[PDB]
Image (cartoon, rainbow over all chains, first blue to last red; front, side, top):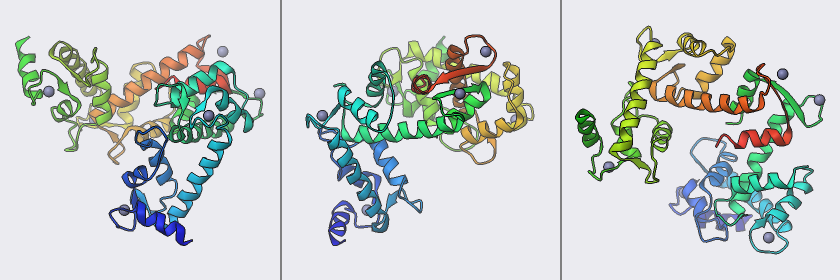
Length: 167
Length: 167
Ligand SMILES: [Zn+2]
Ligand SMILES: [Zn+2]
Ligand SMILES: [Zn+2]
Ligand SMILES: [Zn+2]
Ligand SMILES: [Zn+2]
Ligand SMILES: [Zn+2]
């Protein structure tokens, strides 16, 4: 699509043909007038950078745009008060949606862990990072939960291996 | 001691009265002609920074110097070929020293995880970071190993809590 090319051209400010980490950061809003989470940008870029330039070309940027737009849909679906910030109540709705069974008190930990703003509400950039991290911890857990009952038994050495495979 | 003050003055290059992250990095050698591990410096400084300036004053720097010198002793004690780099064989000696019972194959993972050089040998700056991380993972594990048999049983929610308490 040619519309994607206009976005690419606007984001690719040095006109190198490759959008770097700083450039994608500048083209993204988190609705709080602070710079979009550098770690989130780092995650998104390395997720679509097939070569290793620390950036994306147009061919890969189409995947990046797909990815970011998908998150905007999901964020807004679970943004019911339309506050532009997912609250404790809504974060539960989001996770409960995807089949997570977690105690109310544990959502306090998730919010304190991902919210770079103090407000106890999660912005779009932090929300993406949060879910990416959560997905990875679930995938790892499932390797060790061989009977699918939400419990694992691990030795000290198996535990270290588990923690190190997070990267 | 006045000798510590001469070191402080030489390290504190902007003469601010506080040694920052960049300044401590420059005053430290890892014996490989690459910059001392920024994460290691970050760990050491935040370990002795009682206030929050992202640096250390003379009162705290004495603790920093104590800490770094302690690591130099330990590093050299386990540096038997005097290579200036702890090898797989020596890393086992180091860990076995402090009572760790880990398989030979798992030391491959530790080395691949901490060695920023490719050589499969751990430099001084990476060695400090490695052990700090290992100590923290052991402390956390011990909270969940209530009967002290080197095994833990945890639910998915307990697992997430465990991972998040690493920080
Ligand atoms: Zn560019
Ligand atoms: Zn909302
Ligand atoms: Zn089971
Ligand atoms: Zn200074
Ligand atoms: Zn050696
Ligand atoms: Zn037991």
